Structures are given as C-alpha cells and as structure tokens.
Amino acid sequence: MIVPVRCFSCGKVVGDKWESYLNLLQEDELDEGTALSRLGLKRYCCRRMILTHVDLIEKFLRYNPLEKR
Amino acid sequence: FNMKLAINAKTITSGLKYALATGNWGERAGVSQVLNRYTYSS
Amino acid sequence: RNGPNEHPGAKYVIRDSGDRIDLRYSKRAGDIQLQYGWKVERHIMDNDPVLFNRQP
Amino acid sequence: KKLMAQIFFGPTYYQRLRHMVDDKIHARARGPMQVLTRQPVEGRSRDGGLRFGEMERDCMIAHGAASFLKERLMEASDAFRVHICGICGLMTVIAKLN
Amino acid sequence: VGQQYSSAPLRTVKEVQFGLFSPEEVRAISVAKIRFPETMDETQTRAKIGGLNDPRLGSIDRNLKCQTCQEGMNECPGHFGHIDLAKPVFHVGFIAKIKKVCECVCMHCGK
Amino acid sequence: NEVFSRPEWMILTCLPVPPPPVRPSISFNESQRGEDDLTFKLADILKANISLETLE
Amino acid sequence: NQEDSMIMNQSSIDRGLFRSLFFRSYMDQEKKYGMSITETFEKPQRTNTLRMKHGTYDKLDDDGLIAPGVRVSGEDVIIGKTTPISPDEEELGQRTAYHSKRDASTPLRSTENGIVDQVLVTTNQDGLKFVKVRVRTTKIPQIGDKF
Amino acid sequence: RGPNLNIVLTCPECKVYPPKIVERFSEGDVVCALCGLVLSDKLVDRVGEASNPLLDGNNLSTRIGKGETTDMRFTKELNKAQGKNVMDKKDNEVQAAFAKITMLCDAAELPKIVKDCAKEAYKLCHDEKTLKGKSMESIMAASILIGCRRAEVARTFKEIQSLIHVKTKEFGKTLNIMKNILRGKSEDGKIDTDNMSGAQNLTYIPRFCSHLGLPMQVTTSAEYTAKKCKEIKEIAGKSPITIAVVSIYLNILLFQIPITAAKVGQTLQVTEGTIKSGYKILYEHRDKLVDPQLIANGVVSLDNLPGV
Amino acid sequence: TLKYICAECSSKLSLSRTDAVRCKDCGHRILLKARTKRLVQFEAR
Ligand SMILES: [Zn+2]
Ligand SMILES: [Zn+2]
Ligand SMILES: [Zn+2]
Ligand SMILES: [Zn+2]
Ligand SMILES: [Zn+2]
C-alpha cells in the first residue's frame, strides 16, 4: 500500500526515497532508471523495490474518515 | 373486488429472489453463484 | 508433575477402577501418587511408532 | 567458498496462495460424537476426526495387522456393549445392571 | 469412565442367522404399544405416553433415564414398540417374491 | 425356513416401531425441535391406520 | 526444496515479504420466537445464565459486543446473546430458581485470534437488531504456506 | 405425577452438592472442576425436519409428490385418499387460516414477525366459545392488528380495512374479544406492554411523512410536535390519526414545503376541513409545539406559520 | 449507555438498550461502535 521501509533482499532503507523518486520523475523529467541510479539504488533488488511499488494509500485516502475528531 | 388482493406482488418478488439466491432456476442448478472477491482477476 | 501444558507431559490419569482424571483442574490437590496397574495418558514422545498414510 | 556450479539468479513474480498450513493442521485424541452413529464428528472446525476408509482397511488387511484394524474400528471409534439372548439372537435383553 | 460392569459372560459373535419377524414375536419383543401419532403432550414438557417418543422405548438425552432399564443414554440400547395394522399390508421389498410364490402355489388351497 | 422365515411373514400385520436412538430428534439452536423422517413417516402410518380403523 | 518445495529468506519475511492481512466476519441476529420468546444481546452472568461457554466474558460490554481495537484469542466470546428458557427442565442439575436465561453467544474460532477491527449494529428487513463483527489477523509466511 | 427419570451429575469423591462441573466440549468430557474426575464421557454434540411448536403444536405430516419416475394416476389417487382423513380435518382449518393470514400479510408487505405474531394470536384465540359467531375476516383482521401492534409496527384500522373487507363494528368487537382472550390466557397460563396502548400516535408519523415525501428532519419535528400536542386538553381528545396529521401539516407549513392541505388530506384520507380545524386549535399554542433547538439554530422561526 | 458513530454522517451518539438503532441527526440505520479507549499493545515484529 505504502512504500516499504526496508528492501526485502538486503535491508537497505528505501522508504525515504519515494517522494524524491516521484519528484525526479515529474519535475526533472528523468527516466525511471536514471532516477533510481541518482537516488543511490545500485542493486536491482532495491531498484525493483522502488520501481514496482504501487501506491494504494493514495486511493484509500479518498474515502471519508470513518470516525471524526 | 379488491385489486390489492387480486394482484399479489410477492409472486414476482419471491420468485425472482429465490431464483437468484439459489441456483435452482425454477418457481437447472448452479445458474447463480456467489461472486468471487478473493482477488480482482478472480 | 509436568502436566498437559509442557511436552513431554501427561493429560489424563486412569486408575485401576477405570475412572479417568483430567490433570487440568486436578493440581488443586497436588501431584497424584501413581500405583502399579494404572494408566497415564502421556504425549507421544520420540521413537513412538505411528501409522502414516496418504489417500487415496 | 565459491560454489562449483553457477546459479540462475534473478527477479521473478511470485504469488501467495490461499492455502495455509495453520488453516489445515488439526489433531484429535477424543472429542464430541454425532448423535446418530455415536462416532467422531466430521469437520476440523468442530474438533472432528479423520476417516479410516475402505481403502485404509484394505491396506491394513494386506499388512495383516488384524489387531490394529480392530483397535481402529472399535477403540478409536464407536464401541458399544449389548446384551443378547441365547434363545433369540435379538438384542432385546433388558439389563438392570444396578 | 466407561460403561458399568456386567455379570453376564462376554462372548464373541460367531454366527448370524437371518430371518423374518413373526407377528407374535414382534408383540412379545415390544415393550409398549404406540397408538398416538404425536410426540409430546399438550404442555410440550414431557413425552406423551403411548406416542412416538414413548419414554419406555429409550432415551436420546443425557438428562433423562429410560423407563424400562433405568439406564442412561450411553447404556440403553433402545427398546422396540409395535403398531397393530388395521389390515395386512405387503412388504415393499418382498412384492416380487410374493408374486412368484403366488404364481407357484394355488390361490385357493395353497398346494 | 419353517423356523425362521415363512411365506406368511412376508405380509405385515404388526409393524415394529424402532426406538428413538434409531430416529433421534436433532436440534439447531436447542430452542427449535426437529423430528426424524422416520418419526414423520411413523406418525403418518399411525394416522392412516386410525383412519382405516374408524372407517371400517 | 526437493519435490516442489522452496526455501525462503527469513530476513525478507521479517522485513515484510509476502505478509498478509486476514479479515473474518461474524454475524448475529436477535430472533423473536413468537410473542412470548425473544433473544437479546446481553453479557450473561454465571448466576443467571445456564450452559454458558467456558470462555472468558470479560471483554464484552453492557451491550454484549466487544469494542473495536480489543484483542481476542481462542474461545473468546465476541457477541454475547441470551434467550429465555421454559421451566420444568433440569439438565445435569445445576438448574435453580435463580437461572432464568440461557446463553446463545457466538464464540471466536478456536484456532484463530487477532484484534477486533469494526463492529456495526443495525436492523434487518424485519426490524430485528443484528450485528456484524470483523476481526483482523496477520499471516506471515511459514514452513507450510503455499506459493 | 410420574416417574422421575432424571440424571444428576455429581462427583462421588468430592461429595459437594451442588457440584462444580465443566463441560469440555472439545474433549467430549464432563469433568469435576475441583478434583478433575471425569463424570461422563463420549458426550454427543439432512435426516430430519424442523417445526415450530408454537404455531403448529405437535402435528407430523408428509406430502406426496412426483419423483424421478412416477405415474400421475398413483399421485392423483393417493392425494385423493389422503384428503379424506377425519382426524386431520380439524387442523386443516387452522392451516387454511394460516395460509390466508400469510397471503394478507404478504400483500400488505409486512415483516415476517408481524405475520408470525398474527398466526400465533389466531391460534391462541381460536376454538373458543366467545368467538363462534364472528366472521373469519374479522377474526383475521383483528389478529393482524394485534400482531402489528406487538411488533412495534402498529398499523391503523382504516389501513387494515383497505385490505380486509370488514366493517368497523365487527372489527372492534372481535378485537376486544381477542384482547380479553389473550389477557385471560396470560393470567391463567408476557403479552402486553406500553405498545398495547391504543393511541400510540408517535408510531404513525414516520409512515405518513414517508407517504408525503418529507425529509427526516421534518419527520422528527412532527414527532416532537405530536408528542407535545397531548398537553393541550382541547386536542388530546381527538383521534390519534388526526393528531399526527395536524402535527405533520403544522411542520409542513413551518418548513414551507409546497404541499397543500388538499393533498395532505387526500393522501392520508383525512378531511381538509378537519385538518384546518385542528391547525386552528394548535395555532394558539404554536410556541409549545416547535423544537427549541430548531428555533434557536434558526432553520425556521415561529414566523413561518400563517394563522387565520 | 454506550457511544456509537453514524456510518454516514459520522456523528457520535449515546444509545441505551431501549433506544432504537437509528441516527437522530440524519436517520441512518447503521452505526459503528466507537473504538475502545483502553491502550492495546502491539509488537513491532
Ligand atoms: Zn536491496
Ligand atoms: Zn430371547
Ligand atoms: Zn432402556
Ligand atoms: Zn470432584
Ligand atoms: Zn447520521
């Protein structure tokens, strides 16, 4: 749903690069591979972690909250 | 003569509800099944 | 003494009279004294023979 | 140490299926019996037992374990004591055991 | 716990002799005569005497004893009743056999 | 067989009634009572027999 | 990994490989048997309820329902319901004048456990009150799971 | 007045009476909680049919129908023979009455509980000396009204008459007789609560407002107005139907919903003159017939109520 | 009395055993029980 905190294979921290990856794709008009390389993800285990992630939390946030406060 | 008793809506309502709730297509089997929601492709 | 919650352990104790005692709810009176000819239903331990099957 | 052979290594798409061992594991030493046949109840959700079918009986017959077959069919399942008359084989003997 | 001790000798079934009940044997074996098509009395508290679930035929409850043997559900084997039919009726499983015997014997002297 | 099976016994005059164990009364929530199919058929037999007796 | 088996990385499992949420739903209704008998959601007590389950009723509230977010384990009762009984019926003794209700509660599955997620109370087409309770659990890969 | 035939489970070793007993369903055992001794083992937990011993009592019967192979002659003859039963004739009348009650309730779109209660009331009140000269239509209508009231979905006399063709005199007499019978059996052998009251005008307001298509806010305001309307002696004596209708009309004009009294009375079968007359009485106490929270929030004030 | 929340307008209500299951504000017939206010412990594994 949300970006994983750690890479499954090796344990590198990748949960702090989702916003940077999206910003590189949108504002900088960079390709996915170039953005992944620029973010410091060298091993394809982390490259797939960030490349194949699907952000379903954005869709889940479209529903009105069940409980208010 | 009372039309409310001459026409019984339960005939249509119960017939359709039964035929859809169960697979018995009367009053063939397995015409209606519970939709699979295990996954989107399913 | 180990009882039914620790392997190896026991679950029931059967006296020579045929009556069965559940070790659960029995610790209130303490450990039971065993006598010859009684039966202790104890957990299957290592090297116990068991029949292993696969259908059909 | 390096493996003598080289390993095919790469990403692959894998799926987790609905079958989990924790949802199938079940064992029974004793439990409830059905009202009709007074045999172990069916269904792992109700602490039911496993079926010792005709094929299992045939395999045990081939093995020659007559005592094991009898124990499975009697001690591990329904076992009932009835009183029969010597004149008529009918089990219509009223027994005031007390 | 197990079943209560019995003084009768313990034996093993060696032969099984099949046969058909005679009406006299049915009446003798029966412990009660069922003449009411109901199961419970007007109060729905206890089984009606002479009904289908007559207490003399046994018990299928863990809380009631059998009025015949005074034993629990796990010891009572069950006791048979009987219904005296108004007229004789054929046995559905023996109609063909009865027909063959009728064609084989005379229908006026039985020879 | 003269002793165990005569042709006259293939015709039923006295119908044995099995005990409740053969036809137990099941319960779903224990607040609703269910009766066995054998019990239903035996009740039908009794009603028909009483009707025939009263008629004849 | 012989005969169609596999070896999985325990570190990857710890980091969240092939982990899943399991939601299970239980439904219960207040049935009205005639004008005399009716069932109600309640927290049965040991002094007024007969044949109540051996589980623990500490988690129930005054309405006979567990609030969401509470943890439940095997044999725990999640929906507590009671129905009246007719007199002149004694079972295994233990039936005194104090007892006037009997339990009809819905217990959690013996082998399942988790945290109650969402409980909703409403009325069906017939106007009888019925409730739906959902329980969450986490399934982590094991040495028996299928992939 | 009969044999005991009762089994009581007690621990011989403990001797405590009453005993603490635990039913281990999973292990199929009944165990003493103090010493752990097992008292009874091998305890028990489609082949049968279910029945309700409250509407049918004890009556076991089976139908005859076609199978995978059957001849119509045998089915017809067997059904004919089964029909000519004297013992079963008595209960067939009750079964037919149940069938007609079911048809009426189903055509009325009433919940299952309503028709079940109606059948129970009919069975309880049937076969008595008091109800011997009254029409089955009146009996069924009275039973349906009693069931509707017992189910907290009480309907009105005119609403039930719209389906069952029975005049008011017979309907009321039968209803009173049935209520007396129910009270007598409740005492000798509960039955009634606050719902058994006659007026209960609060229950009608939601359905009338639904018929008129008003919003739930207007429905709640009308409920409050009707609840407070009983404090005026000049209106408390009026029929509950009129009280509810007048309250609904007052709230309709309070919220300025474009529905005229000519249509309100036409939809709820109430005279427009009666509606306006009741509005005249309630206008003198409009101040006590409006929700303080509503008037404070300002959705509407007392002003939006024309007075003649 | 116990606290519930409407399933549509998300209003907190205080319901008793006698009160009907219904939202007094909008009229919705579905209510979700309010989350328990007692802390629940979770392991970070
Ligand atoms: Zn990595
Ligand atoms: Zn004999
Ligand atoms: Zn007996
Ligand atoms: Zn004891
Ligand atoms: Zn709401």
Image (cartoon, coloured by chain):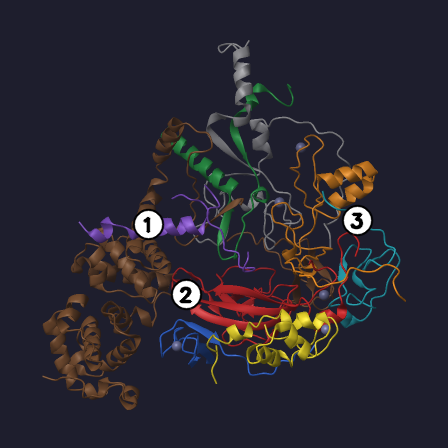
Instruction: List x then y, in percent, for residue A23.
Output: 58, 80
x 83%, y 64%: residue: C8
Examine the rendered structure and indicate whether residue E33 appears above or below residue B18.
above
Tell me, by letter, which chain the rendering colours yellow: A
Tell me, by letter, which chain the rendering colours brown: H
Q: Does residue E81 appear to the left or right of C9 in the view shown? A: left
Name the residue beneath numbered marker 1: B12
- The residue closer to the viewer here, H83 or A30, is A30
The image quadrant of residue E87 is top left
x 14%, y 73%: residue: H261
Circle 2 or circle 1, nearest the eye: 1
Q: Which mark is residue G128?
A: 2
Q: Which mark is residue D17?
A: none
Pointers 1 and 3 in contact (C-beta within 8 Å): no
Q: Amino acid at mark 3?
A: Phe
Q: Secondary structure at mark 2?
A: loop
- The residue closer to the viewer here, E70 or C29, is C29
Q: Secondary structure at mark 1?
A: helix
Instruction: List x then y, in percent, for residue H178.
Output: 28, 59
Name the residue beneath numbered marker 3: C52
Q: Are marks 3 and 2 on the same chain?
A: no
Shade representing chain I? blue
Shade representing chain F? green
Shade representing chain G? red
Instruction: List x then y, in percent, for residue G22.
Output: 60, 66
